[PDB]
Length: 115
Image (cartoon, rainbow, N blue to C red):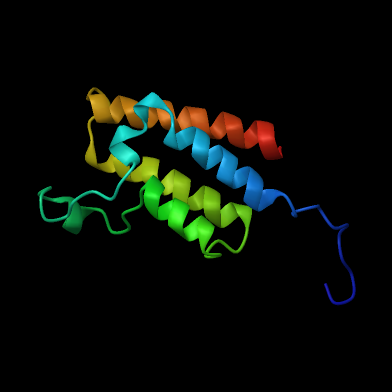
């Protein structure tokens, strides 16, 4: 509260470390559904159904331009990529499986790096 602060957790490396994680996600073999924004002209249903599209390229641009205020807003966008994928894709499809795999991969790197 006012003039009463918990000890300062060092956040000075968060930007670099989120960039590293994102590089690892970008280079994973199962990243291909997620690298670029879904083409809303070419994929029926996507525009109306997925209220907040997100993709790795869009997160990389946001990261690079100071549009994440802290590491939690970065994690929220990453998880949005996978939550969107689950909303639109059956579990038993290549893309549906890709998304489960990538989410698992991310969440381990996240825990190992920060928790």
